Image (tube, helix red, strand yellow):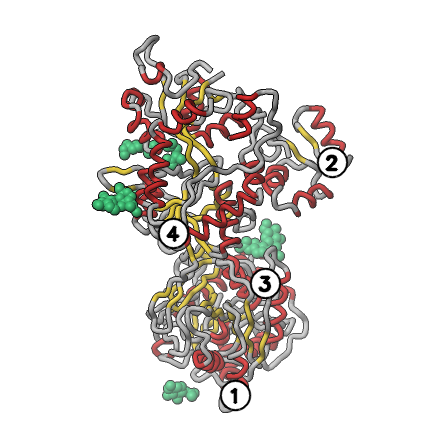
Amino acid sequence: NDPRLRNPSDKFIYATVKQSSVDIYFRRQVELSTMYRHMEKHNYESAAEAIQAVRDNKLHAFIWDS
Amino acid sequence: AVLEFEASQKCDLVTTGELFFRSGFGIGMRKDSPWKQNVSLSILKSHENGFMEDLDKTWVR
Amino acid sequence: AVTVAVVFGSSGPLQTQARTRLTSQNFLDLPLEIQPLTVGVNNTNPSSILTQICGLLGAARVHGIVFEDNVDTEAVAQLLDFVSSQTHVPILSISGGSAVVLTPKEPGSAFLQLGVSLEQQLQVLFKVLEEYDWSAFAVITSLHPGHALFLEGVRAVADASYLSWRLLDVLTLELGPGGPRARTQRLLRQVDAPVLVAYCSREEAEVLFAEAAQAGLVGPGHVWLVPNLALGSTDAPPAAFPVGLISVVTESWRLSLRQKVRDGVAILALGAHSYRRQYGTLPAPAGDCRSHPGPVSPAREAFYRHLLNVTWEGRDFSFSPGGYLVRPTMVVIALNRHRLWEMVGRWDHGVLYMKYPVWPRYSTSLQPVVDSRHLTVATLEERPFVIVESPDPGTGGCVPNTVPCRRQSNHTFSSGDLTPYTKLCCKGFCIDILKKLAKVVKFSYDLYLVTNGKHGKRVRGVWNGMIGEVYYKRADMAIGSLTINEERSEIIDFSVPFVETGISVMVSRDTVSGLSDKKFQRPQDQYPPFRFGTVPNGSTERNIRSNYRDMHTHMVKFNQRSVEDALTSLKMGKLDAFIYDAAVLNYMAGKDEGCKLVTIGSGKVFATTGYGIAMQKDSHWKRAIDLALLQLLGDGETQKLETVWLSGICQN
Ligand SMILES: *[C@@H]1O[C@H](CO)[C@@H](O[C@@H]2O[C@H](CO)[C@@H](O)[C@H](O)[C@H]2NC(C)=O)[C@H](O)[C@H]1NC(C)=O
Ligand SMILES: *[C@@H]1O[C@H](CO)[C@@H](O[C@@H]2O[C@H](CO)[C@@H](O)[C@H](O)[C@H]2NC(C)=O)[C@H](O)[C@H]1NC(C)=O
Ligand SMILES: *[C@@H]1O[C@H](CO)[C@@H](O)[C@H](O)[C@H]1NC(C)=O
Ligand SMILES: *[C@@H]1O[C@H](CO)[C@@H](O)[C@H](O)[C@H]1NC(C)=O
Ligand SMILES: *[C@@H]1O[C@H](CO)[C@@H](O)[C@H](O)[C@H]1NC(C)=O
Ligand SMILES: N[C@@H](CCC(=O)O)C(=O)O
């Protein structure tokens, strides 16, 4: 519900793994449609490379299982 | 509008939280009263020139 | 030694049609030296067709055949497929009843019909239904053969879609000459769906439409959709067809016979040319019916495979393995008031463009009816509240939770016949409010932007912008960032404000502390002139002009524009104070990297007013919309919209 997430910008980048449960969760939601559209353009192939990108600072935030 | 004035004037009391039902005060008349528009126009004019600012400053400090 | 035969079967002026050209100099633009041959089947009976085709094959040894006949034909497509299976000659049927698609075709046969299957027509019709948001339709069907395939296609297309279609009921009829008339009449008086889809032959279509006219299913409260089969000669439609009938056809619509013949010969010539480029030689000529070449002759299979995928004059002529046109551009045509088949929309690639943003409906007396519950809403782009985007190219349409909107059609962007309007998608706070109002008050609406001025200012006694559109009855209501003020409330009516706002001051991080400060009221009081300005032609400018003459006379120097540009000029240092709307200034402060601040902690909003929904003076919708807005404010939906649309980063 943070306004940085709900109001996306080219500058901010957050994404999740492609074709996963989080992808489905954001697809189903209608009030999260803008977030899904922003996320889909930068979605990652796997979780480990997503962690490496986060440590790299290429990806600001990573949404994944707890 | 009333609670904030009471808290400011009488002190010793505090208002908590943010406003959870935003509305306005309005002049009430019978249904389909012919001179509604008049009053509404006047009220809008009072908002435009200076009248509501003076009324706020003079009464609700 | 390439030889291409054209067979004319149309029962009109066939001799005038065969004689039309019967030449070899034609088809010059082609990557080949055509050698045509007109045989013109005289009457298109099975014996005549078989005998003439066999004689042609046993005399000229043609490489391919192009067939053409009239639209009343029913069973010739079977005979042509039979001939192609028996002699292994590639035929190509163009126009007439021979161009209806047969789905299973004699596996070893190259028929290659130049028509579109039933499923693609169903897809186009369902996308037409999606465009105007028509649901709860009913299906009318006769006992015409292939109706099971039609129903299965309807069910598959309805099931495999993102929208939630809702079929009401399917009714089967006889629609035969001289039979039970009470049964059809009784069944037709029991349907109440607003959208009806029918599937039958030409004569059955005429019978059904006559019965429906007797049953009161023709007026403006009923829209009919039919596939190609129900249509006949498009040039002369019958009187039984109701005005507003919708169908979907290929580009061959409105083309002349010679053009169709040229296109077929071109397809065959390009297939042969590709075969020659690939194998260095021409394909073998066809044999004769007094034999049976059991072996598949892989040379002929290769020729057929080359003939499948071929393009000509920028149009795709690819054929499905089922021998019909795959992914062709199709046009959606409708029967207008003049009782002519006007073309309405197009189906280029997987996306749909349609001429009419709203479907017209005419009375039973051909009198244009306008639905009283369809409101025309004018609006304008304002980043916090109204956002316009281009539709997603991938899916044709755009993302849900985004209402389609059109741009003003004053300037025609048709470029021929594509679309006279720019189709965008609008979203945001005001559009969400409008959607909630449409759900609650139960009305339908379109949405178009205003390209004639900003929100509105009286110039030379006339009004431009949204106020101009509403006052001059071009639109039912105006929604957006419209401030309630006396000069507008006198000329038009206003609804209850749904978000409060006013005049506010923006500075780069409390030097002024008041709109009526001596710095503003007296520009030349001290220091070189204060560089403060505002966007002209708005409520703020008129308020300043009518109240503080010195303020307005100084503000003329700094006539800012494009509030984002004013904001960036403030950031750079070309400006030190910006006078504008409080609702947008709070949002602009919220999503600021430097976190610009409004003059006083709460901005000390001056001339407090609100955003309203403009309406025509003394209208009817006013009371209902006022009550609906008050209900929305009462139930906390407006607070939810504030949280989801006007949140800020450093506002807390
Ligand atoms: C609202 O105010 C307007 C003034 O702008 C009133 O209009 C005048 O009304 C009087 C008597 O009703 C007339 O003699 C004047 O000729 C009107 N002026 C104009 C310019 O038309 C209006 O009547 C008021 N509304 C009501 C219900 O009294
Ligand atoms: C139609 O498609 C066929 C194949 O589906 C194309 O023929 C191929 O052409 C490429 C050229 O690089 C060859 O490598 C393949 O071996 C060919 N395949 C076959 C089965 O012939 C043909 O070129 C296409 N038509 C056009 C006009 O491009
Ligand atoms: C073909 O039709 C013409 C006139 O339409 C007729 O004169 C001719 O005899 C016909 N040929 C046949 C039936 O073989
Ligand atoms: C329509 O467009 C023309 C430009 O072709 C321009 O004068 C103006 O935007 C419009 N003219 C009107 C509304 O008279
Ligand atoms: C404001 O109106 C003036 C005069 O009509 C015009 O020249 C100016 O371009 C307008 N400013 C806008 C539309 O931002
Ligand atoms: N809401 C304002 C637009 C901003 C302004 O010009 O003050 C109006 O409709 O007048």
Nearer the observer: mark 4 or 2; the answer is 4
For the residues labelled 2 and 3, the Cα–Cα distance comes to 43 Å
Where ligand 1 lies, by quadrant? top left
Residue at the image position 67 percent from the left and 24 percent from the top = A57
Can you identify the residue that label 4 sits on?
B32
Disc 4 crowd rating (10 Å Cα; few below 14, some 14-19, many 20+) is: few
Q: The residue tagged with tag 3: helix, strand or loop?
A: loop
| Residue C371 locus on image (x, y percent) | 41, 62
Q: Residues at marks 3 and 4, common chain?
A: no
Which chain does the residue under circle 3 lie in? C
The picture quadrant where one finds residue A52 is: top right
Can you identify the residue that label 1 sits on?
C182
Amino acid at pointer 3 = Ser
For the residues labelled 2 and 1, the Cα–Cα distance comes to 65 Å
Can you identify the residue that label 2 sits on?
A64
| Residue C110 locus on image (x, y percent) | 58, 69
Residue at the image position 42 percent from the left and 21 percent from the top = C569
Amino acid at pointer 1 = Ala
Amino acid at pointer 2 = Trp
Q: Residues at marks 4 and 1, common chain?
A: no
The residue lying furthest to the top in this view is C527
Can you identify the residue that label 3 sits on?
C320
